[PDB]
Image (cartoon, rainbow over all chains, first blue to last red; front, side, top):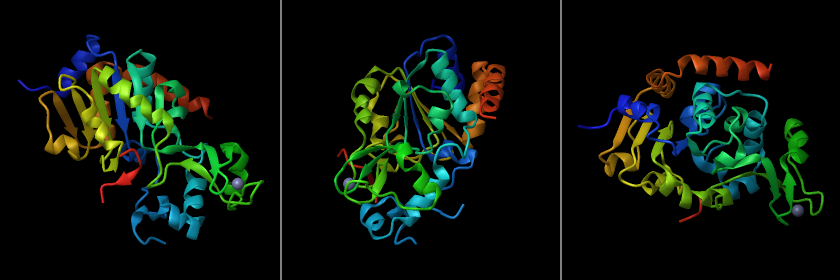
Length: 266
Length: 8
Ligand SMILES: [Zn+2]
């Protein structure tokens, strides 16, 4: 018959799937307290202005307040991140692609080599005028003092390396040409798949590769181009991952990891 | 089609 969440967990437990590629979005960051990027406040021509360069040049204060909130150290990873961390620790993670900019994937312990922050990061920054690169730390203070970072060379605005609309995606994104054909399982956690070219990556896997979606809604290419080995665990993203963790037998090992990695951060 | 863009 058709594949179920239990059948995919059985495939993982049997080690039939060992090249898992994961795609994640805001659905896995909202349970950690990350605010919705469309509904601010925890100045909008349209919701996407916060990540649009012309507005940013008109008024960059809204983006830099959002950053002061999302900059590392404030929020902390949740169960979904530590599940993916466990996938990596067990040698099953080929690569984790994320649309999120909170850095919680790195904080959960996933090494940068196994991670593709496809929509940029606050760890680096670039001057909007002369393109001079800068370490993300070199501008941290300015954002905490509610300032606007400025280039020490040309006085232009320095922008964290968050990929804005219209901007190219980082170069580590181009690892998708080799990873997705090499994947034997595709997990899609908490994303509406409305942003391209990220969303189109669901189709970059082979039709013999299962695609498991844990998201409140069946969204995007999985709804209009369904495949035989597609599985959809619709509902809350945390409960869906916890159901998969139980079906995998990782509940207690998770409970150990979540308590030890959290206390490490005091 | 390598540049970030929303469906709309
Ligand atoms: Zn400059």
